[PDB]
Length: 75
Length: 77
Image 1 (cartoon, chains in turn blue, red):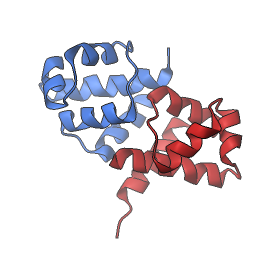
Image 2 (cartoon, each protein chain N blue to C red):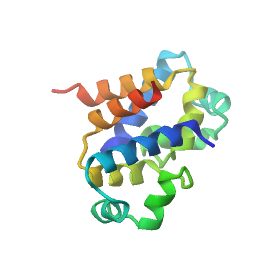
Image 3 (cartoon, rainbow over the protein chains, first blue to last red):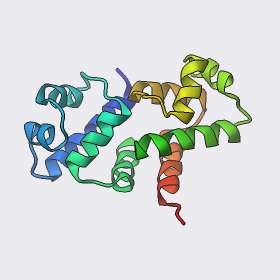
Image 4 (cartoon, each protein chain N blue to C red):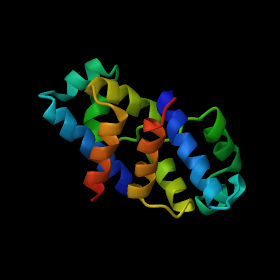
């Protein structure tokens, strides 16, 4: 696997979960397919920087907060 | 993509800090020069894997990189 993917995908789930949000929820707010959101979260899809931004607007989370929560998961 | 803009920028910064050129980082990170240039201007679309690849070309942690990312995000005026 890719250790990075692991941790990005993890912080996505966390926040998605923190947001009382489901997968098809986030698929809907973020303009992607649910298929894609499941996959991503089992480290079974490869997301580009765009999809990540799309996702971050689905999540309603800034880039500072996200990446602060990313480093924390690295730790 | 505003994000691309600031990721790409921290890449160049550290690459530069590292007395490193683009084909240098293409070499160490095991990508194509073509894409390293592309990334740093048109911020060509890099995936999370490519980022990790590049991050090991750069010899920089995930903590320092992302600390340097936020900073580029936070700096203003």
